[PDB]
Length: 108
Length: 292
Image 1 (tube, rainbow over the protein chains, first blue to last red):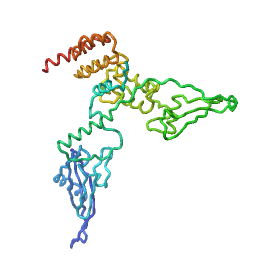
Image 2: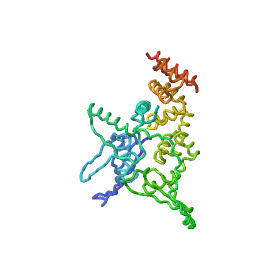
Image 3: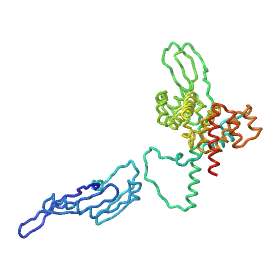
Image 4: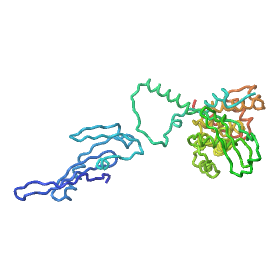
């Protein structure tokens, strides 16, 4: 009951089926966390989007990371990280400075 | 004799009385924060850093000068009655010259009365505050020094703040300075809150105003209850330095003196409530025989 989930990205994805012509799937990328430092995310995909929200929920509890927080708010030290054509950079702030981030990263 | 705050005896005794608390000395402040700086140190480097801290804390801890009151200065430099009929409201002439000590500045006035008068003290100060703006100072006196606001700030146990407010706003020899400092001491006394200003730079003012008000009560009681003997010792020592000739002084000195004998003889010879001292001076004593 402690785990909140947020939908990061819902997307309409298509395929080519000999029978049907186009075939429409929905894929949602979803994250989950308790606020206490452990959290994770997963992808899920289904024909009906409701189904897919469900799928990502459950699969995401299965991958959790523990995220270590300094004095239980910031990160410990600056992080500059290049991952696959995307660069992430994050500075460790003091207390009055709430969450200045990409909207996704705020959510996470 | 010549005792005063700036004497070495009074100084070293009041520094020792005050105490170094690096937590209360350096405490979180409300200013816009910056991200914290980190470095890895040896035992040695941490010790040297610690001493560095203590050194710098002393400077933070330096006592605000206590001084006697200033008398009103009334002197007229000239009179021409011919000007009087101009019936114009007051003119205020200040000198602003960057070399000058602000007690050596010349501040003058011409009233509608056609006379050349020197500026009064309050007047003089608010003038210098206009042309030499210094932070924290209002040029018109801040409301908070009304009795209501005073009591409100005392309730909130903010007394360090008030005493920090007067240091900046008024002048150490002023009337208001003295009124507020002293009244504030009266409050910590009637509330027994003395340990507030303990690691503060304000402690010197606590000690003095009381030795000269000859009520050492709460501070001695508290010191013995806080399990500090040496402080009560140097404090009676102080009452002896600011009162050399009295029964208590010369008798409880020349007879013999140390922790037990001088603190208890000055507990018998200062009668405000000697029953309080004698009670607590027993308790600490008892709490020794159990701990040793």
